[PDB]
Length: 157
Length: 159
Ligand SMILES: [Cu+2]
Ligand SMILES: [Cu+2]
Image (cartoon, rainbow over all chains, first blue to last red; front, side, top):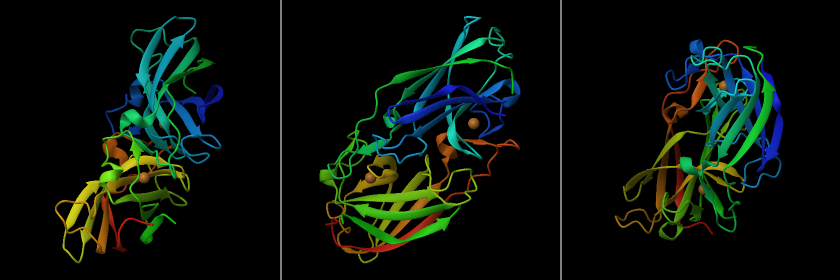
């Protein structure tokens, strides 16, 4: 059962939603933390809005973007930063990562009201290009921006 | 038109693979790909998810993080040149393409003539792209590396 975090934000021609489920077994194995040692699979859902500035058709998934997350507990004041890898499930491509909450050895990441950030950079760092000719070129990529959600952690769904 | 179709599309491994080549295209960041002034065409590969894609990609979606290598052989001059097609976005959506020197190649043999185009396609796992493999949200294995063939006549930069 997937649980929404806050509600989506529409900026830079993209709909940015936050969701998390139970830890998810992943392949290739070894890159992302093992589902056995995690408490959640935090997924970032980012799709091009209608009339996207950068030529991405409406509803398409936005690939090659660099997503760094920050996980703050308002009650705990404990925060850790990590990365969200590009992943695909049976419902479509997305960005995700398994994170250990209750199992965070240093604690403070179990129970709590939470603040979730997404630090989003454009695909150019990953070698992704774009046309800039007058006939088929598209606009500039957004500059790095941040997105913040508020959610209260319920344990594993 | 400004855009030339190459052969006919292929429907394999849950994807539609089509090829088209353009005039040389100016693209940023500059330096990654051969500059448009030094090229004669812009070869592009259009790859999208078919209906009921075995790897969880919605119908019509662009297939990202793919490793696409191309081989262009002038059947009449026997010349062969290889390269890779980068992920890039135009005004009509993302694709894989590259600026290629044909008549402008110094080794010669890539002028007008009959051509055999081949794409060498490997799955996204080499880029670190992930897969759900749980019972509820899991998707099937990725295809093994394969290739598709096109044939077309080249008579210079599209017009
Ligand atoms: Cu996921
Ligand atoms: Cu292109």
